[PDB]
Length: 232
Length: 232
Image (tube, rainbow over all chains, first blue to last red; front, side):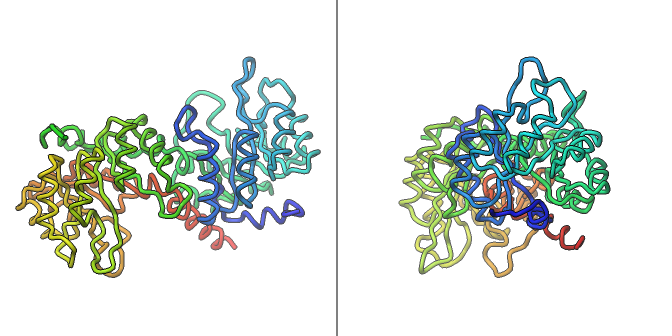
């Protein structure tokens, strides 16, 4: 009811930073109460959308905020490298929990259920679908399936060696192809995020730089401890 | 009480980012159990010291972590612009709560207790004293009083228009004077924090960029929303 169609959401999210609230696993901060508190806080600060992981987290956050939620479930599978929403049971639970958008790994890797079935299942719930992509080919497949949103989420996370810079070229390619493009992955500063917008993204999703305190702490200490070594 | 000597603490803090855990006042995150969770998290992430505000918060954090706490109590007073640790009773409360360092407003402004008396009260507890300074003369005064640590904490927060850039010149001046210098105030990125170290700071205290989620969120949206408007 809040969004009648995908074009309304696209206008709503134009130029927005979407806050992915996924604390470090095993941290004292990885607690539903703290995730909900962070969600409330960023809504009050003006954030227009969130990415939340876990069905019960999606349910708790949707009860506390009014802005739309992009829902995922992350799993460690025994026979597959796919992690982001790999089962239709996860799709069902995320929709029932109140996700507005459901995101899923759209790579063509070994997986327990076909990416076609995942995308179908999302569409049947009435949630918008978001394809977390690693290459341009992934998003072209997603668009061919009627997936509403394509993200660069998994670029740099499928092969050898994590790049450090964001994949701007994938964002440009997606947007020039007319896709509703979500820049996602390593946009660690407002300047890099803004550049994703200028590269054609509708919106940019930011996680670590906002909601992984341990990671940002280490960014700072890596810089200061190196400066203290140089001075020495 | 505290039994370390200042030279030990200097070696311990050299090159270090000190995490000031002061959530936005009134935030759903401005809660003792969340402040404790963040303190534990950053200790786990490798941080070597904290700044904590509030006697109860200092007590709860010092019970949960090993790393040393720079303790303050912030009060907005009707008859004075001084906010940071304005009373001897706050000094005593912070020492009893487990602070290793007690920081205090070292400006020469109208205040309910003299800065000499606050500094002497800290000395009497056995805690190290840290002068939160706005100008070089504040730090020269503090050094004359035997205060062990001099910070640039209040530079830009005593006049009218707050700068956006950090006061590198005050850090340089304090370090050139031979003071145990803590850079503090608007070191919003790892690179800026590193430049404080390069400018002669022993350590740099970072608050907003790590522990004010609402502030960092607006930093991101400021940039992306501006890029989105330029596009449109």
